[PDB]
Image (tube, coloured by chain):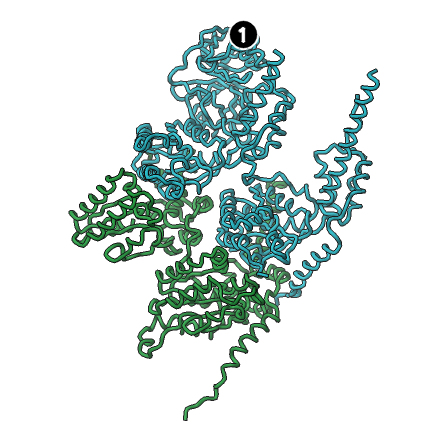
Chain colours: A green, B cyan
Amino acid sequence: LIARAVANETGAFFFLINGPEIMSKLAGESESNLRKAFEEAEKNAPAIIFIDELDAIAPKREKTHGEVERRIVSQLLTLMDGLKQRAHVIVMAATNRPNSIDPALRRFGRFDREVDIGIPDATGRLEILQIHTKNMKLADDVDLEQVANETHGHVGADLAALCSEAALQAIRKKMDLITIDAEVMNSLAVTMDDFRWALSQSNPSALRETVVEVPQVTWEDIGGLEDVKRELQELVQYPVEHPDKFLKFGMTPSKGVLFYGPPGCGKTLLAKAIANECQANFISIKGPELLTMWFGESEANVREIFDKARQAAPCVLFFDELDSIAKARGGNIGDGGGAADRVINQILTEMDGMSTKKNVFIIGATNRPDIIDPAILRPGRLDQLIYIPLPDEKSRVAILKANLRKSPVAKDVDLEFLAKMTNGFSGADLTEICQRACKLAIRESIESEIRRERERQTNPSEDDPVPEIRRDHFEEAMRFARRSVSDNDIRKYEMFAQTLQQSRGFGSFRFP
Amino acid sequence: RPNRLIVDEAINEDNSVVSLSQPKMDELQLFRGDTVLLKGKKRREAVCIVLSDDTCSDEKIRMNRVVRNNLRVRLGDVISIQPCPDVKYGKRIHVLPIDDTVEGITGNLFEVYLKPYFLEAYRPIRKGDIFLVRGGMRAVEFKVVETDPSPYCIVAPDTVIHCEGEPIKREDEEESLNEVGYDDIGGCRKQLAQIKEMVELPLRHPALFKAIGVKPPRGILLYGPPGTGKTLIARAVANETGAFFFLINGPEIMSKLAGESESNLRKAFEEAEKNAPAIIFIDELDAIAPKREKTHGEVERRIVSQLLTLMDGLKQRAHVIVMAATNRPNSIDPALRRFGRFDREVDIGIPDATGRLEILQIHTKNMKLADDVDLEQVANETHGHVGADLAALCSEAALQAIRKKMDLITIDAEVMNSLAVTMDDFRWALSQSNPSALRETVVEVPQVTWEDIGGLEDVKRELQELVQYPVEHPDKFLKFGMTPSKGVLFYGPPGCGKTLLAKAIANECQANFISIKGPELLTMWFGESEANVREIFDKARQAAPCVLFFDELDSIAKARGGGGGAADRVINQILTEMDGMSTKKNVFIIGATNRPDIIDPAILRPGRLDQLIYIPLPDEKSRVAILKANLRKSPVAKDVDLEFLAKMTNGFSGADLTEICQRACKLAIRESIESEIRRERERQTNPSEDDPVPEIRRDHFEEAMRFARRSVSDNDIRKYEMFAQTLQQSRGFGSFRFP
């Protein structure tokens, strides 16, 4: 669609080469078809030759077993090289991944410009839904924003299928009741019922794909930590907002930072917030992914990750648990080996090879800064160490408000008081309290609905019993509230930070 | 016009019964037994008895395939329903067999087929109607070429029921009942409904879809173990929708010479194009287009590319749906699963006990089974049987009966009808079964209920809140803006009903239940096949709503010692799959572990098995319920006081109570066998009855309690209680009151 739209809007002649179609033809006929396509593009220049499923024609040389396949790949390379004489003919080609095709095609003069379409974000999904529902008559009930937010893992073909499924659900509903009359279609409409049913029946095709998008988190979602906000700004926003200042003062922007602190205190929230403030893409590498690379010895994939971060820049590449592999080896005492491991070694290799001009910022997070490999805290690496402590009262209030944003909460509740009485609670604990309150409210609502329906059953002869989460709901939820971070863990983190700070003497330094 | 009604699938198998929804006969003013002359296409009339039912929709009329065919209508069509009081009885009806259906049956065809039909059953018969009599083990079609009070008559004992020989030739516009239909398919009612909803609109209303201008389903990939009748499903869908059916056989295509295979594929797609709307079924798709790695020759890749090209070119073909059969989604080239290709998918899977019973009824439909057989018992005992396996089992039972008859003794139909299969034959066939899907993962709604495990009311409430509420009240969760919990972790002494609890909660929500035992996790760990975890979750995703149960999450931790950390490859993959699990899908993860201490902490984080539920040893009421459930299928003397037995079994796990019940049952069996041996020995020594032990007596339970052991020591209970108390003590802040 992108290639055809570009050709149509620029007025260029569009020629489509389907890889499977080329490979379907007998030996020699594939070469003839490729040559004829390129000749036709030459004749109608300016032209765009779009090769769909390029990996079908020219996969990795290992995947090309037959001699005719290699001959076809060589013919494609020859045509790409001969483009030099072919006046203003551009060849676009679709592929699943850059490594899916023969590397010889990615050389200069051949497919050298590359664009990663990737997966649409919530805004992108909303745009796609609006495009595919343009003709569709939709009831005022449907808000495509909610569908876009809920359609994670969809690519656009998935969204088109979802819209078609909703339309067909509506048509099925209105078909048994009733060449076909367009008045029925105008009357026909789709509601959130149809769209939610389609969402339930939809099978996203890009759930495994890495998410690369600007996070919707903001500094308000995590109050307090103003000093951490300032440090993150200086380390991410300034190099991208004011490269001129860094050039003038001749400083190299820091490549990354390492968050350390109690679990579930908002390190991920902080990384997403700083990515959002700079409107930079955010890539999250969770601890399970690092452990998957370590167990499977797939540390090569680390390179791919960084490529992704390089491809979508400026970026905040976030490693949720850098100590995950260290813990998996024992961590506190570990095995007989040292702190170095294959996956973290590859991370260091990629960080060293990162061009600072690309504005890709690495943020590591760890609840065990002691067991992190020291080689990653060196200059030119995650040199800065930032302590993310347990949220303070203002931070707790902000976290509670952020959690209770999609939940209708009675004005009677004093979130300020609740935050006041939750000293020592991590953000995870506050989220647990809010979820418990929502659980109690939902249970009360369902029980009241059951009682009402039973009353109707016993008496054939309506308002929401509980439309909001009430003061009593939170009071009950606080009974199950627990502090996941004990005072001993806080002491450990405070001792680590104090050890780091004590070495920072020489503060009584003054020029003469 | 009230007479307009939509044809629908029948429940009752009678060929002259049309069911109607309860609020509709009154509107049309019927009498639950009145003769109604339904009108269909081609100016076809069929007179039938109108029954009543609840499941039927107000505007829907349930019709069996025979009445549908003689009315020249299909499911979803519109027919005119109106009473036919002028249905007076008749004197002579000239029925005649169809040539095809009696091609090899010799006999009277009356007192065997036409007599049991119409006997004590006043079936209204219209001239030209074709009715099916399923007797012996054939299904004979009989066409009424003449009735004395034409066109409609009622068969009565005072009727000639005249018939002759010379079977007539089936006319062009007659769809032989031997053709596959939805009634010929069992064990995939859910998947069959999915496929029907997918393909009915594009096929039943092609031009309406074209003017519609919305994307139709192009490729439907039915996977599941072989023998589940996927070809049967496709053929039935094509027949019931009137769509042209073209069968492409993978091996047949690959057998042809290079180029001839391409020509065959192209010609198949062209033929489907011509006779649109059409269904192209590609049986054994993996044969044509396996994983590219499996494909070696140039011709193989060329034929795969040709198939992809045809699938992509479907866009210009008039309402042609391509269905393909495969063992697993990964068995075929990934390029086939792209959009514009086999993007729609259905997992037929192995049938469940209900599905197995449906299949057995379908395959024994013609069989003149003895009254002794209860197909429910066979369906319950045929675990691991695909539809093909059950067909083979029914065939083997019939062959056993035929062999016995031949030993007692082109063939007379009377003895064939007399020939009856008994539960002895079915059990013999079950012994010589060799099911083909014993190792396939079982995905079904468990039959366990909360009654099988009494007590644990708080655990019942938690499980309900965590599983039933999100699937039964999504609106509430949306309103309150809560994300349903992804899963829970049961912990407690072994054999205390954790599996029972998971199965019970799955049953209450009528959700599929997938059990992953500790040996499976250890197999993935030892073989380093943790990738299989993904497949498991995929399966669970395919069967949503589902309760994915991990019986021993600590199995790998135990296998490692219970020097490294708690992380391991298999549990790491479980974490990865759980994180990538969309909460919109109602897949609920339940983990069970006798050793919560050695469980990887990463699994207990929010967004994972965050809730920890302690399943203690059964209390007295739970013990009574466990004893009752264990002995449900065992004849137990009324003298036994299960309440007293539960009272005296404090500290016993559910496994211990099951052991006691099994010990008593085995003692009773031993006593029965010894008494029978003694009785036959006496008969031999004194040739010269009643069951010596018809039930498990109280003495048997008293003897069994001698060997009764407490599998869970007080120290283990202390450990679990200490764990629970450590969890609880952290949950302070109870004295929190808003100002």
Query: Which quadrant is the C terminus of chain B positioned in?
Result: bottom right
Image location of residue A75, percent across then percent down: 24, 47
Instruction: Identify which residue is drawn at 43% across, 24% down.
Output: B79
Examine the image and state in which quarter residue B708 appears: top right
Secondary structure under tag 1 reads loop
* In front of the other: A389 or B29: A389
Circle 1 sits on which residue? B159
Q: Is residue A509 above or below residue A269?
A: below
* In front of the other: B411 or B359: B411
Image location of residue A10, percent across then percent down: 21, 53
Q: Tell me the chain of label 1.
A: B
Instruction: Identify which residue is drawn at 62% across, 14% down.
Output: B407
Image location of residue B380, percent across then percent down: 61, 32
* Extreme residue toward the bottom, this view: A512
Q: Is residue B1 above or below residue B450?
A: above
Work out whether residue B26 can be spotted: no
